[PDB]
Length: 188
Length: 188
Ligand SMILES: O=P(O)(O)OC[C@@H](O)[C@@H](O)[C@H](O)[C@@H](O)CO
Ligand SMILES: O=P(O)(O)OC[C@@H](O)[C@@H](O)[C@H](O)[C@@H](O)CO
Ligand SMILES: [Zn+2]
Ligand SMILES: [Zn+2]
Ligand SMILES: [Zn+2]
Image (cartoon, rainbow over all chains, first blue to last red; front, side, top):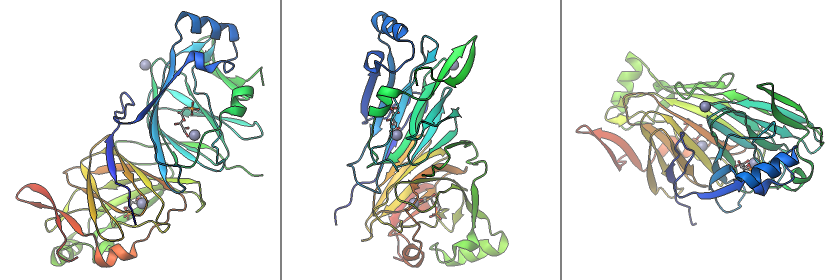
């Protein structure tokens, strides 16, 4: 039998960078129809088009039982009152769970079942989050610096962004009067 | 249908402690027939029987697609010339991979195929080790302080200790003349 090579790689807990990883970049312009305030989205995209997040992914072939891992650097920012977040997805194989290891910054995760019932888990350095089977998941940076975490996921989990792209989450995370609020999404 | 509850838990990267996790403890007496120097083992068990390592495990039902995670605190020490290590295991479902995230200390992982061919990976804080399908794996603390890491594995991976308990690994990690050597196992 042919065996894959074991390997070690350095992850910098300060920057989220993994040498030799597939680097992915999500600009604000790539997230049309994601934020509640459309005119604020339009305004910030034309003024700056900030990078919302970067992903450093170490991925195997899509084989059951095997594991991928990836860091996300989610940048600090707001669209209107709404904090920067990742697009959010269900796994293509829905029952595939996931483990997040928060490394730096302050954020949290919004999770949601196919039926639209949502949950908010705060994340700070050292917070390990268990994303159970079937839960869509989006990370949010509620802070002033990059929110950096490591995600470990089944290599055959895949990524389904379609349903979230159109409907979003049932809850949104906003700053009102200087305070972080998880409130119902008006657009849901 | 019923959905499992998402949750976050604090992991102290300094201590390896996971609040509310299942705690397992391995002392030297729990490791009979593991170390090369049979008489050194006996002496230490009778005098002290020190804790070799501790595991904090957050586990789900044994279900495909799900994930478990566990920290290990591998204490520093030697049996004869041979560094403290974990028992080592194959996964019961052999094709199940694993990811380790080194958190504190200095150490490494010994891996071995069903054939007996070996690989050594050095681990220091920040090192992420990819443990491929079919590789047995054992961690070793080659330093003076606790070696702490987080492991993330398929919830249906299982733990096969049998083969390793009787024959060990093909290589041993030892200190000869103040230097750390990965040499052939004579009792193999
Ligand atoms: O894939 P996104 O929603 O744009 O959030 C982006 C990434 O953090 C995300 O891929 C993360 O690595 C895992 O959840 C993958 O299963
Ligand atoms: O299972 P052990 O050899 O007694 O070393 C003990 C632990 O480090 C070990 O359970 C680790 O969590 C993972 O490899 C489990 O798949
Ligand atoms: Zn995911
Ligand atoms: Zn800050
Ligand atoms: Zn294992």
